[PDB]
Image (cartoon, rainbow, N blue to C red):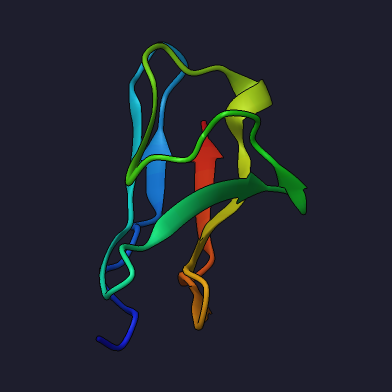
Length: 85
């Protein structure tokens, strides 16, 4: 079945100390895999539908997206901006 992202991440405007929660959910068979990126670099070990940072600071500001893939198809989520004010 067609790999397709159904839940797209959302941009957020956060304060230091707030929680960052990004989500990307896809359907498909074979079952989709995920890998999150920030500022063009993979976030190590962030291979889940959720990416969550409990207490944010300025270092978490940036542009994020998730690569979603299986052994036939792949899609990139929308790019979202996390602003830390």
